[PDB]
Every structure is written in C-alpha cells, then in structure tokens.
Amino acid sequence: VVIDRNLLILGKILGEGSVMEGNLKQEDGTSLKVAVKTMKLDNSSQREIEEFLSEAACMKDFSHPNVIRLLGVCIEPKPMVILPFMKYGDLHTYLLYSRLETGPKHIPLQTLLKFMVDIALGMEYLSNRNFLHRDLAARNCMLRDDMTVCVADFGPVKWIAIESLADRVYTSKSDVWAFGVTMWEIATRGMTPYPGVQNHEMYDYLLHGHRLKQPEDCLDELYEIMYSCWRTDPLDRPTFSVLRLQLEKLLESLPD
Ligand SMILES: CCCCNc1ncc(C(=O)NCc2ccc(S(N)(=O)=O)cc2)c(N[C@H]2CC[C@H](O)CC2)n1
Ligand SMILES: [Cl-]
Ligand SMILES: [Cl-]
Ligand SMILES: [Cl-]
C-alpha cells in the first residue's frame, strides 16, 4: 500500500485533517492526477495507525465502479491517503449548482434515482465484505468522469442513527440510516437535513418518533423506501441489497 513519496507532487488545497491535489507518477511512466488526504492520528501508540494500515490493505483490493479506488499511502511522520481526482467534484455541490443557471440543468427524477442506485451498489459491495463507512453523506459521494456516483471518504449528528447516539454503536444498518438521509439530500437537491431543528435537539426529536419530512415533488413510493431506513429497530431496516433493487425497480418504471 505504501508508495515512495518522491512519486508524489502536491499542490493546491481542495478541502479543510485536510485534502490536497497532486500528481502521482505511475509505474507506466505516466503522471496521474490524484487527491491527497492527510491523516492526524494519535502517535502516542501504534493502535490507530495499525488499524489504518489494515484498512488500507483492504481498501486497495476493492474494485467496483461505484466505489472509490485507493492508490496507496505516502509518508513524509504523517501518512497521506492517495485517491483519484474528480474534476466534477462531490455530489452535494453539484445539486446546488443545478438550481442555478450557467451550471448544470434541472436534474430530472430519473437522473436523481440513478445516483441512489450507484451509492446503493457501492454500499452493497462494502456490506458483503462487512466494511463500514461511518460517514455516508452527499458531500462524500464523488462524481466520476462518466457522471456516475461513487462512495468515498470512508476511514454530523443529523446523519448518525438514533442507536448510534445513545449506545454509540455502529453496524451496517447504521449506514443505511445515513444512506436514507443521502437519498433525502438528492431528492431535495442539497437541502440541510431537519430544517428548524438544531444538532443538540436531534436525539429527543428522533426518539419521539419524528423523522425527515417528505419533499413536495417526491413520490410516495420513494419516501417509503427513505422512511424504511429510519425505523427505530435496526433489524426492521432493509439491507443495501434490497434498497438497490427497489430503486432499480422504481427507476425502470419511469420513462426516459
Ligand atoms: C473523499 C475524497 C474524494 C476523492 N478525491 C477528490 N476528488 C475531487 C475533489 C474535488 O473537490 N474536485 C473539484 C475540483 C475541480 C477542479 C479543480 S482544478 N483542477 O481547477 O484546480 C480542483 C478541484 C476532492 N476534494 C473534496 C474536498 C472536500 C472533501 O469533503 C471531499 C473531496 N477530492
Ligand atoms: Cl511535493
Ligand atoms: Cl438548501
Ligand atoms: Cl424534515
């Protein structure tokens, strides 16, 4: 997983650890445009870095068109996660530009659902290998050059599941919760979850049975899938394999 630091040239800041652009000189002699995420670990012990290196070995062997690839790691002693570059950027920002001229056109419902299928397919790939994201959101979903969504940033209380707020436990269904919110952001084209509610009022809001409201133009069939991911009991929540097929079935039922 480790790559020689001399093969990496850094540049601008893309986000703020932090994120940086760069050029990875491959083995075939060609320079590849890549993103570089810094990692602030606790160097008081080799506990965090061990788990970081273990995941890197697995995150590199992954191969799926709806899951971001991991190129390797570079040491300066801070590590740096090397990832592919995405000129189209994240999905959340793309949804905000769509509601503005000059930028993308008004995204139809058919295109919005395709994003959900991709994300679902990405999480379905990780679920089979028992890999948790623990940070699923629209801001984390990047767009490939062929306009296909891919999950990323897998090492925000309104994205965390109710059980993960009390017992602070994280299972596969905890990502289904975040996936449910992700579907809400896409349908709403970049709205912040739970308008009117603060981050410190969430645990009591959800515990009382309240959930994210249904959008104005959102179909009743889609909200049911979105609401099924927010059920109090994680066991009652569906898996990504189910959600993936449900969205595909609803997608094909629509015209072009
Ligand atoms: C989780 C990391 C995602 C994988 N790598 C990645 N890819 C793209 C971006 C990004 O922001 N692209 C937009 C962009 C477009 C043009 C240029 S240019 N060539 O004009 O200077 C630079 C950037 C990216 N950065 C994001 C930073 C915030 C973070 O939350 C998500 C990723 N990362
Ligand atoms: Cl450099
Ligand atoms: Cl908004
Ligand atoms: Cl709401």
Image: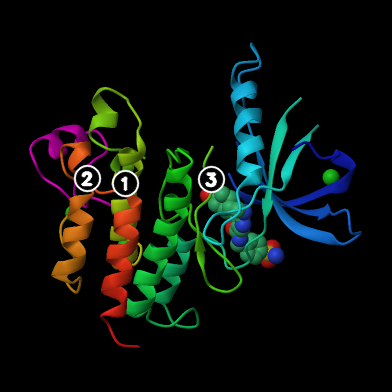
Q: Is the stretch drawn in magenta largely helix, strand or loop? A: loop
Q: Secondary structure at mark 1?
A: helix
Q: Residue furthest left?
A: 208
Q: Give the spatial CA distance, label 1 vs label 2.
A: 8 Å
Q: Which residues are magenta?
A: 193-211
- Which quadrant holds the N terminus? top right
Q: Residues within 10 Å of mark 2 (few under 14, many from 20)?
A: many
- Magenta span contains residue 209: yes
Q: Is mark 2 within 8 Å of ligand 4?
A: no
Q: Which mark is residue 69?
A: none
Q: Nearer the viewer, mark 1 or mark 2?
A: 2
Mark closer to the chain start, 3 or 2: 3
Q: Is mark 3 within 8 Å of ligand 1?
A: yes
Q: Which residue is mark 3?
A: 153
Left/right placement of residue 148 relative to residue 49 reads: left
Left/right placement of residue 8 relative to residue 176 reads: right
Q: Give the spatial CA distance, label 1 vs label 3.
A: 16 Å
Along the line of sight, which residue is nearer the eye, 218 or 169?
A: 169
Q: Residue at x 12, y 34 (%)?
A: 207
Q: Give the spatial CA distance, label 3 vs label 2.
A: 24 Å
Q: Position of residue 122 (x, y in %)?
A: 47, 55
Mark closer to the chain start, 1 or 2: 1
Q: Which residue is mark 1?
A: 176
Q: Are marks 1 and 2 in contact (CB under 8 Å)?
A: yes
- Residue type at mark 3 is Asp
Q: Which residue is mark 2?
A: 237
